[PDB]
Image (spheres, coloured by chain):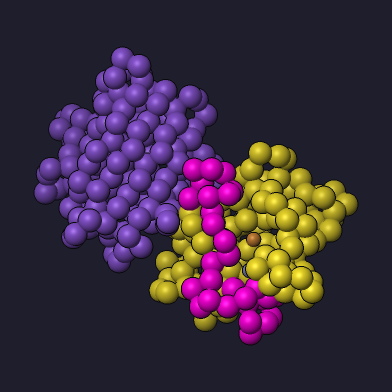
Chain colours: A purple, B yellow
Amino acid sequence: ATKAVCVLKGDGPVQGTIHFEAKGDTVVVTGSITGLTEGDHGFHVHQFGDNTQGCTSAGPHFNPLSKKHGGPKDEERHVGDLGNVTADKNGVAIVDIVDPLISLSGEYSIIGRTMVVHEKPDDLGRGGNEESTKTGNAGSRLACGVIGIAK
Amino acid sequence: ATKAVCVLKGDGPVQGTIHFEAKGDTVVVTGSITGLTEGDHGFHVHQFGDNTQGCTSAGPHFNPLSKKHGGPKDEERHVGDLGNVTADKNGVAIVDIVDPLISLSGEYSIIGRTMVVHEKPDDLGRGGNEESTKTGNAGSRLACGVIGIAK
Ligand SMILES: [Cu+2]
Ligand SMILES: [Cu+2]
Ligand SMILES: [Zn+2]
Ligand SMILES: [Zn+2]
């Protein structure tokens, strides 16, 4: 696949549409999310594209290389760690990321997995408690969607 | 990828959870759909896992081999043609399908595509008209969901 899309929905007002495109050897992530509180929100690819229990059955971060959580720029990060998206005054976050670890095919493929937008800022694995090394203290899953093949 | 799951949702009362498991060279499809009118309903894998416009953005049946519409037991069928599911008087259809053409990996992989349950019975390509050979005359998309990787 060269293009993927994900529609984020949850139990509150958070909603959004993320597009994924393979450009060269990398993947470009674009889109926008509305209904968010102002500030940073953890944005990650969770392992399972299972929405049987809402965002909860999405499991933990996609991590085929079995590393600890980190920011998008660290070496020690989960493949699913895309950092934070930032909502403005109006609750709108515009997504514009380029990432070297996720893919739309092969072992690092995120097609069929779940994009999750979190309630709090991701601390990038530097919070200092065990939880930081797992989820960055990003908190609850406000909205999520299964990543599908797009036209 | 040996297991997948799909949660079907739409704008009406139809809902369901479909599970997929690779067994030998086949995919075993199980689950249930509720809120359906009694009788047969076409059940197919549509090409895109794009839910930006509901079930409509899912595109047509998944047909990598450029064949016409048929029933699951036909040689001339789309890879996404799984036939019909049957809802009882209470509106519940129990799904139990074994299929050798769809797959959870490789070229015919349905991971990231869309499972759709339709309003009318699928005529299996034997309706006598032209639509019969494209869609089985299954009617509207009652509920759909993106097929994701399951634990
Ligand atoms: Cu997360
Ligand atoms: Cu169909
Ligand atoms: Zn992580
Ligand atoms: Zn068909």
Q: Quadrant of residue A145?
A: top left
Q: Residue at x 26, y 26 (%)?
A: A86
In which quadrant is the N terminus of chain A drawn? bottom left
Q: Quadrant of residue B77?
A: bottom right
Res. A117 in view: yes
Q: Is residue A95 above or below residue A29?
A: above
Residue B122 belongs to magenta span: no
Magenta span covers which residues? B50-78
Q: Is residue B70 above or below residue A146?
A: below
Q: Position of residue A45 (x, y in %)?
A: 33, 46
Between A121 and A19, which is closer to the camera in this rendering? A19
Q: Is residue A27 above or below residue B111?
A: above
Q: Residue at x 37, y 31 (%)?
A: A33
Q: Position of residue B146 (x, y in %)?
A: 51, 53
In which quadrant is the C terminus of chain A drawn? bottom left
Classify residue B128 as left or right of residue A89.
Answer: right
Classify residue B111 as left or right of residue A19.
Answer: right
Q: Quadrant of residue A8?
A: top left
| Extreme residue in the top direction | A89
Q: Residue at x 20, y 46 (%)?
A: A98
Residue B73 belongs to magenta span: yes
Q: Residue at x 54, y 57 (%)?
A: B59
Q: Position of residue A136 (x, y in %)?
A: 25, 34
Q: Position of residue A70 (x, y in %)?
A: 18, 41
Between B76 and A27, which is closer to the camera in this rendering? B76
| Extreme residue in the bottom direction | B75
| Dominant secondary structure (helix, strand or loop) of the stretch shown in magenta | loop
Res. A69 in view: no
| Extreme residue in the right direction | B89
